Image 1: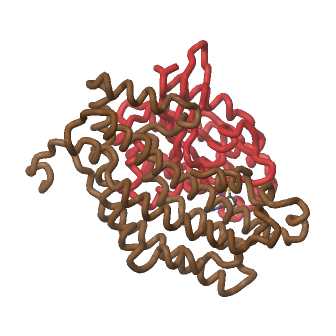
Image 2: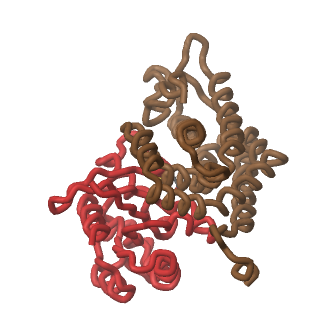
Image 3: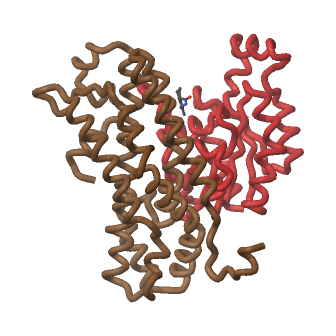
Amino acid sequence: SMEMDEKDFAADSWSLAVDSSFLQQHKKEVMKQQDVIYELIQTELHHVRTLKIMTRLFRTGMLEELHLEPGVVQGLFPCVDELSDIHTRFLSQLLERRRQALCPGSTRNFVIHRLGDLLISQFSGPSAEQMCKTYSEFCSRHSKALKLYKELYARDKRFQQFIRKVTRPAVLKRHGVQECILLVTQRITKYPLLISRILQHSHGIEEERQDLTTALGLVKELLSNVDEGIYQLEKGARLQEIYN
Amino acid sequence: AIRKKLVIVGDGACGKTCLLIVFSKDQFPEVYVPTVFENYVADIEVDGKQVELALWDTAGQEDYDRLRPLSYPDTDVILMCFSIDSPDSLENIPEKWTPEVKHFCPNVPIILVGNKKDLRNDEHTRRELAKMKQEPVKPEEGRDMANRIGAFGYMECSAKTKDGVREVFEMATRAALQ
Ligand SMILES: CNC(=O)[C@H]1CCCc2sc(C)nc21
């Protein structure tokens, strides 16, 4: 992540991120809705940061420093480029919606009144098809990626030294190769929890309550489709095992 | 320092996310309680041994039977949560969660944890439950369930008051080590 965005999301909540004199001007219900919206963006920034560690630090680091067999690096980080593109675009729109909402003369005081429209766009049409396609593929290759990681760490000395070296910094404490893969898989199921709590505090405007209710239903339809398209791939799985 | 993986399982309103947050922050959030928990790596020293314990949640994964098991690979200790203000969450333990945890995590120790023990003395809790011919889960009922399912142990805590939270994770570390 970039420093501009890290500072905007360093606070534990929206009520702590905005100026105290700006906060005082708002009703409690707005503050509560804004806190959950801030959490949705902050965790999306962290999710995008996880995907950059997988592509730039791990994947590219392995390609430019190790002599692994062709196709090994793809098996360790499946669909990471497609995933990073999907989520960097969604984060871009979330951050642009916050920036348009800033008060003049301020880089921290904002209120997001419209969010449902953006969530309906993300979880509908071709963007929903690409997320469904990419997560079904990713989550079916999850087990095979972990097993491949365990084989390489146990047998190759240069792979073990590479991993120990790039994950040694404290900022990487909870971001190893296996942690990144579970962090990515778990992400999709966090959206209905976040959207339902935003909806809980968005009854003031009827259009907003309806857009969020639609977006919630779209996310659940996507999660149900991803879940139905999953079948764990095994390295060296015979055909007889697959069709039985 | 060895690396151990803990996964917390349980029904939606069992309070598992709140338990992980209060432990990871090491206090009850005063300004905003987060909706979600990503992950955390705890630095714990139990009985002289230093362990790096990775903390994970299954929250949001309850209706997704093919997504949920992806949280189980390489687990060293399972926290099986239920809410003391919800006797129906305890009934789901032996027929819903226990068969799943034992298939995907064979031989892994399970600690049955009763959350929200503070609500055992809440008057609104007792009144709401009596309207459905119910009462808060008694300590002996929790121990009997932990015994019936073959749990490593039975523990109780209150994430709101922080009571018994440090002890559940120190014990989980010990179970992961055996
Ligand atoms: C998203 N569902 C919830 O119940 C929200 C609303 C109340 C406050 C909290 S704390 C938590 C883990 N979720 C919620």
